[PDB]
Image 1 (tube, rainbow, N blue to C red):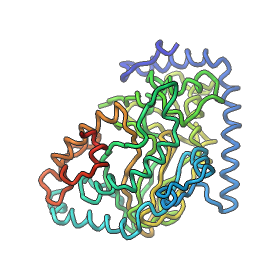
Image 2: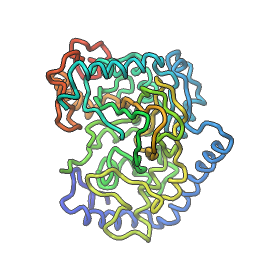
Image 3: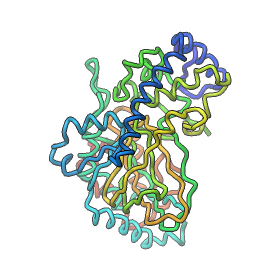
Image 4: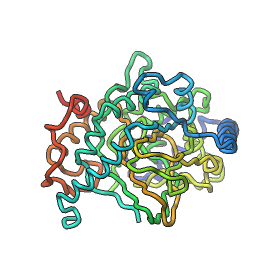
Length: 403
């Protein structure tokens, strides 16, 4: 059924593959419209909960204290909330002064190496500052990643899909937005693949209960086969992330062009079935295109867009997280008040796929070169004060697949 249209790599004729995919899946579903209507009603109950919370001024994003994570005192109710909303805010993951200190440390590292001489939001092509790497291999980050990964069912049918207690080092850039920044923001979308979610054999397995109409049996927290997903290479993320996330390096004020998410992890089911309805052109996938993130819009997903929810006010040191299937955006802002500085650090549990990238990460770290999933700029190759292999602690070594 799936073999008639699936492909482990980018199909030579994606439109033809899409057409066959639609024919095959519509046949399997039988009455996709009825299934979609029921799914819409179920998702609507969640949207209602979200609107009720907003009306009460109550928090929508689950909020947990790092203190509880560290002490191992997060309640079952709290864990349940994260599984229901697909996201979380970890308060005081790092002391506020530590987070602010890291931001200043990176700036001093840039000055020391005359960045301005060798090089309105802006992403820095820097990956190996001591602040960035120490944060990544910190006990605090390790504890949070373990906690988050364990919300997933990673063991099923006598097989462990990933090690929740060790996450690979996924070097990313730091973003800094000073007061006065004006940005159009980013439209709602999801990562971890677009067209792949329909054509990759691995995703057909992951979403088997979505595409066969047995939605009641689809669990967004089931890990099976997600570790086998390989994003297409078009003209790009090489790791499996359970959660995307970032740590605040500055306080983040309400309404100042902030991250928003649709706190309904199962919303992806609606996204996957939408292109199968009767008002979609044969060759189209509601905006999806090779080489671009999967877009979510009012045009195609009105029910989902209504649920977009901003992160609450944050203090530097807090971290925010969202399930890999969660729809997210960044609201526009004009003459931003306060700062908007963040450090991207996800949760990517060790597995065959992530170990392969870990080896590449280790090599880049040794040279100070830009990581594989990023542009080849290699600014830090001759920089001083850089974090090196000699600075790795035991957690960092495991996170790099080292002995």
